[PDB]
Image: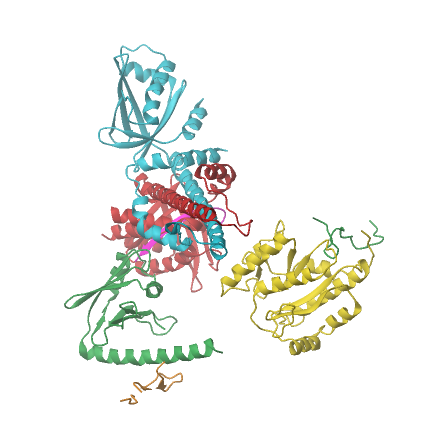
Chain colours: A cyan, B yellow, C green, D red, E orange
């Protein structure tokens, strides 16, 4: 029961969340028996694992007039949250607001179902070092290593293509389109050019949007490989 | 021509001994096999198409006692001195010319060849280090030979520092063994097989 | 052969030369690190002090025991040196390492710079002679297949009777 | 201000691999005459320490008594002992290292022979704060990943241009001589599909952190420097 | 390669340096 929630949270991708002119990175896994949430702002990480009993206790106090079982409440919350996390610029009927009191983040979500109000607050405390490491550090290092291997493969392919082009150049003819001439690929020169020209913009994490938009499949694959 | 321990056999003498052992083994196992001996890096030269620094000591012909004696004339220190005097040593060379000379020697013969093999006895992991065009020419010639149907193998000899195949010879050999990408601090194990004389006639 | 380089870079005639002295290796006399830069008419020296050395090392994220000579030599090899001359001060920017380094230099007194200039000239002549001599000396002066018979498996050597 | 310079120096320094008696760690140390700052990790937890001259002198007196040295000399000797190990490993060190993981804290003991005499030091590294841990590991890693993705995209564009040039050569009444030197068209989707199932399992294995220090340190240093310059 | 020489050229540091230029050529020491 509890372990399934942790595995689901681990096997989930990061999503961008907008609230009150602020940004967050959220990973949520919701099942009928509870849910797990991990929210980061590139400076701190908060985690919350919740079971059905506490779900009912908190829901009955947040929505006094709501008479629902924990499973139905969790299903409704998942149906409300997943569409927003999956993509933006959609019919977002839910409003989010995050606040820090002392060391724990309270994330309040307010929406309307069938036109009636619906509130839910995540009281996520600071994530433990082990959870933060397992969820961010090791997957990121694996992604970096995989990308370096991809760069090496691309360099080898470029070398082979350059060898073929040189074969044509040394024994062959001249291109009808002289504009297509390509310079030989040198790894050191390319790396130097990249570092001095485009690294400042390439390494601009910003508010976390590029991390979510650009590379998430690689993160999921690395996490899955780590699990196995 | 340098001995590291001052007591072990020099690479050239050991290569000559291996060639002699192969000749003796062939004289019994199969009298209808063709063997040739070519030296590259010498001052003198003699080839059908006349490149430079390539000496073809013996063309492709059936083994015989005369060839064994010719090899024996360079057996030891006196043999090494005679070889240096008659041929010379320590000159620049390009592998492309050597490989093309070997191809010409292979093409010269008329008897149908079941196998075409080349043996490279050297202790230079990176021959064309300063130059780069020569290395590329060597790779192209090796690829052409491999596509033609000629199998090239290297018997690396003692290296005072260390012999590495990943530098230049990785793409030169026909087929790479399962575990041959490491650095070899000792002579190739195939040398023992070559020196192991076999006295028995085998029929196809 | 202390590291040094001449500016401006290119085929144009030189107009400035910079070098570093100090941090001598071994157990002999050791002097504080310093930089001497001359146009052949005026000389600028760091005039560093141990507190100045510590402040400079800590400013650029460099440990106190760290040696700056390798970085200076590497930058000189890469020709990543830039200069900005003021009325009486000079600023040197080095980009040979991962992080840029800034150095401040002040004009050396003439009476003290002249012996320094003479020593620099003598040293340069000695290095020229040594390197010319060195250049003159160096520039010119299937598994289980028999290898012998392909197509036949290599028969194992005849052992004979080997009692267990 | 001295603490600020120590923090900046620690941020600038790259990760290094340290081999203790039984385990391994990733460490970054910055030592100046005013003190030092150290950050160690084992890919599961991060510990940080930062000490000033007074603490250094007290610790030196309490650990190795009968030694009367100013804190600056002790810090210089510690740097001389540590920096060579971090720069390169598997070399003559004669400096034993050990770690004790006490409750919610770590003690890193280093023993050496200073001119033939004992020299002991202990780093009392407490759990690193989330802010420092994030700034030192998470954001730089994300920046490195983004930079590598940009590099991959650039290489793909270069491959596409080379493929276009090859197509032009082929269509310009040409005839390839060496058929073996024949590169197939490059497709991003096919290459990614092949990679994710052929090389990702072996290319995403961090292990003990040795590949990270051996491969992705220059990029890490550049990203950290860029972040520092930005803010 | 303008010729030049130093005295002493041995291990002792050189004292004087001699050269020639512009073959109004004058030997400069």
**Image location of residue B38, percent across then percent down:** 67, 67
**Image location of residue A13, percent across then percent down:** 39, 31
Between D38 and C56, the residue placed more toward the observer is: C56
Magenta-colored segment: predominant secondary structure: strand
Q: Determine whether E15 is above or below A152 in the image.
A: below
Q: Which residues are magenta?
A: D19-32
**Residue D209 in view (yes/no):** no
**Residue D109 in view (yes/no):** yes
Q: Quadrant of the N terminus of chain A?
A: top left
Between A39 and D39, the residue placed more toward the observer is: A39
Between D86 and A29, the residue placed more toward the observer is: A29
Residue D29 sits inside the magenta stretch? yes
* Residue A85 in which image quadrant: top left
Residue A156 sits inside the magenta stretch? no
Q: Determine whether D56 is above or below A222 in the image.
A: below
**Image location of residue E24, percent across then percent down:** 26, 89
Query: At 43% across and 77% down in the image, what residue appears?
Result: C135
Query: At 16% across and 66% down in the image, what residue appears?
Result: C86
Whether residue C59 sits left or right of residue C134 in the image: it is left
**Image location of residue C93, percent across then percent down:** 25, 61
Query: At 82% across and 60% down in the image, what residue appears?
Result: B28
């Amino acid at each position: 029961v509890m372990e399934e929630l942790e595995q689901g949270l681990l096997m989930q991708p990061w999503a961008w969340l907008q609230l009150a002119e602020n940004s967050l990175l959220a990973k949520v896994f919701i099942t009928k028996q509870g849910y797990a949430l991990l929210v980061s702002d590139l400076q701190q990480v908060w985690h919350e694992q919740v079971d059905t009993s506490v779900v009912s206790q908190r829901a009955k106090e947040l929505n006094k007039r709501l008479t629902a079982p924990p499973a139905a409440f969790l299903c409704h919350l998942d149906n409300l949250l997943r569409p927003l996390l999956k993509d933006a610029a959609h019919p977002s009927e839910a409003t989010f607001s995050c606040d820090c009191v002392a060391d724990a983040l309270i994330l309040r979500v307010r929406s309307e179902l069938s036109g009636l109000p619906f509130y839910w607050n995540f009281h996520c405390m600071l994530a433990s070092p082990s959870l933060v490491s397992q969820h961010l550090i090791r997957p990121l290092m694996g992604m970096s290593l995989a990308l370096q291997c991809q760069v090496r493969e691309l360099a080898t392919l470029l070398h082979m293509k350059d060898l073929e082009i040189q074969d044509y150049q040394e024994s062959g003819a001249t291109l009808i389109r002289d504009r297509l001439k390509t310079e030989p690929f040198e790894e050191n020169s390319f790396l130097e050019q990249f570092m001095i020209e485009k690294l400042p913009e390439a390494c601009s994490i910003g508010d976390g949007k590029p991390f979510v938009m650009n590379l998430q499949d690689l993160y999921m694959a690395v996490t899955t490989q780590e699990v196995q | 021509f340098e001995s590291q321990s001052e007591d072990e056999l020099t690479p050239f003498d050991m290569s000559i001994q291996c060639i002699q052992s192969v000749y003796i083994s062939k004289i019994i196992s199969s009298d209808r096999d063709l063997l040739a001996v070519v030296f590259y890096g010498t001052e003198k030269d003699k080839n059908s198409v006349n490149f430079k620094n390539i000496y073809v000591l013996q063309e492709l012909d059936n083994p015989g006692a005369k060839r064994i004696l010719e090899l024996d004339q360079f057996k030891g220190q006196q043999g090494q001195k005679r070889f240096q005097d008659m041929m010379g040593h320590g000159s620049d060379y390009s592998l492309s010319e050597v490989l093309w000379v070997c191809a010409n020697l292979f093409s010269d013969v008329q008897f149908k060849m079941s196998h075409k093999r080349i043996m490279l006895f050297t202790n230079e992991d990176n021959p064309h280090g300063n130059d780069s065009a020569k290395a590329s020419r060597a790779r192209t010639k090796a690829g052409d030979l491999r596509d033609t149907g000629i199998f090239l193998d290297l018997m690396h000899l003692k290296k005072p520092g260390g012999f590495d195949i990943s530098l230049f010879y990785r793409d030169i050999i026909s087929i790479a063994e399962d575990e041959d990408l490491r650095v070899h601090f000792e002579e190739s194990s195939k040398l023992e097989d070559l020196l192991r004389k076999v006295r028995a006639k085998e029929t196809r | 052969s202390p590291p040094l380089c001449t500016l401006p870079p290119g085929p144009e005639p030189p107009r400035f030369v910079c070098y570093c002295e100090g941090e001598e290796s071994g157990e002999g006399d050791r002097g504080g690190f310093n930089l001497y830069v001359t146009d052949a008419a005026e000389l600028w020296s760091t005039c560093f002090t141990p507190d100045s050395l510590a402040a400079l090392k800590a400013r650029f994220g460099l440990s106190a025991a760290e040696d700056i000579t390798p970085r200076f030599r590497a930058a000189c090899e890469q020709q990543a040196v830039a200069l900005t001359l003021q009325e009486d001060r000079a600023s040197l920017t080095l980009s040979g390492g991962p992080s840029a380094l800034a150095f401040d230099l002040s004009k050396v007194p003439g009476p003290e710079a002249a012996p320094r200039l003479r020593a620099l000239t003598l040293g340069l002549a000695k290095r020229v002679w040594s390197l010319e001599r060195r250049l003159a000396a160096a520039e010119e002066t299937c598994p289980g297949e028999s290898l012998i018979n392909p197509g036949f498996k290599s028969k194992k050597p005849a052992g004979g009777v080997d009692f267990d």
